[PDB]
Length: 264
Ligand SMILES: *C/C=C(C)/C=C/C=C(C)/C=C/C1=C(C)CCCC1(C)C
Ligand SMILES: CCCCCCCC/C=C\CCCCCCCC(=O)O
Ligand SMILES: CCCCCCCC/C=C\CCCCCCCC(=O)O
Ligand SMILES: [Cl-]
Ligand SMILES: [Cl-]
Image 1: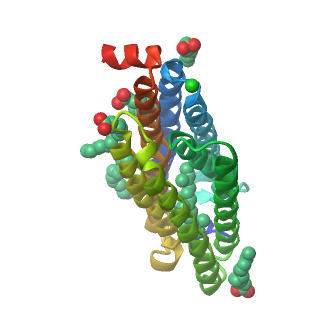
Image 2: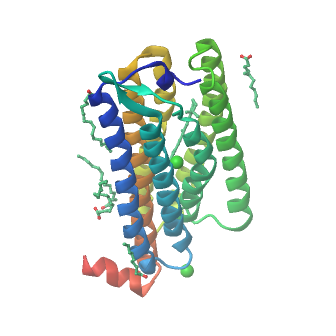
Image 3: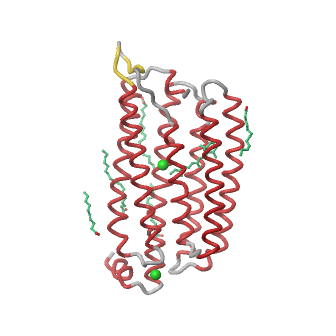
C-alpha cells in the first residue's frame, strides 16, 4: 500500500499532478525527435549512445503516460474533492521501469567514455548488477511506506549502499577514462558525473517523502521531485551524452559530425 491511496485531493492538487505527468510525456517525446534526427551526425563508434537516448525517451515517456492515465482512472470528483475509485495508483511501476532505463543510461556513458571489449562488458555487468540491487531493494522498501516506516528505512539503507557502490564505479570510470576523450569532452564528462550525482539523489529523497511529509501535499512533492529528476537524469543527461558523442565524432574525423557542428 502506497501513501497516495490515503488521501482525497483538492481539484488543484489533482490537476497539478496530472499536468506534471502530461508535461513529462511531452518533454520526453519532443526530446526523442531531437535524438533521432541528430543520430545521423554521430560516428558509428558512438551511434548506440544516441540510440539509447531514444530508447530511454520512449521508455520514460510511456511510464509517465501510463502513470497519467492511472492517476485519472483512480480518482473522480465526488462531493467537492477527487476521491479514490476502484482502480489504484502507485509508484511501483516506475521502479519496474528503472530495471531497463538505468542500465541504458549507464551504457550510454560507458560508450562515450571509449570503453570497449572485455572492459566494457565487465564494467556494464557490475554496474547493472549494482543498479538492479538498488532498484529491487528500493521496490521492496516502498511496499512498506504506509504499514511500516522502519522497514522502508532499512530497505532504503540497503538500497543506498548499492547506490553508493554504483556511483563509485561510475566516478572511477569517468575520472580514469577522461584522458582518452577527444575534442575537449574530457572537461564535459566531469559535468556529466556531477549532473548524475545531483539528479539521481532526488530519487531517494522522493522515496523518503512518506517519512517526513505523509499528507496530500507530500504526494504532490514526490511527483514534482520525480519530474525534476526524470528531466535532469534522462533528457538533460541525454543531451550532454549526445553533445559528447558528436564532438568526439568530429574530432575523430567523421565528416557528417564536422558539417553538423560547423552549421551551428
Ligand atoms: C531515469 C530514472 C533514474 C535515473 C532512476 C534512478 C533511481 C535511483 C538513483 C533510485 C535510488 C533509490 C535509493 C538510493 C534509495 C531508496 C530507494 C531508490 C530505489 C528510490
Ligand atoms: C529541470 C526542471 C524541470 C521541472 C519543471 C517543473 C516546473 C513546474 C513546477 C512547479 C511550479 C509550482 C506550482 C505550484 C504548485 C501548486 C500547489 C498545489 O498543488 O496546490
Ligand atoms: C502535452 C505536453 C506539452 C508538450 C511539451 C512540448 C514542449 C517541448 C519543449 C522542450 C523539450 C526538450 C526537447 C529537447 C531538445 C533540445 C533543444 C535544444 O537544442 O536546446
Ligand atoms: Cl566509428
Ligand atoms: Cl524510467
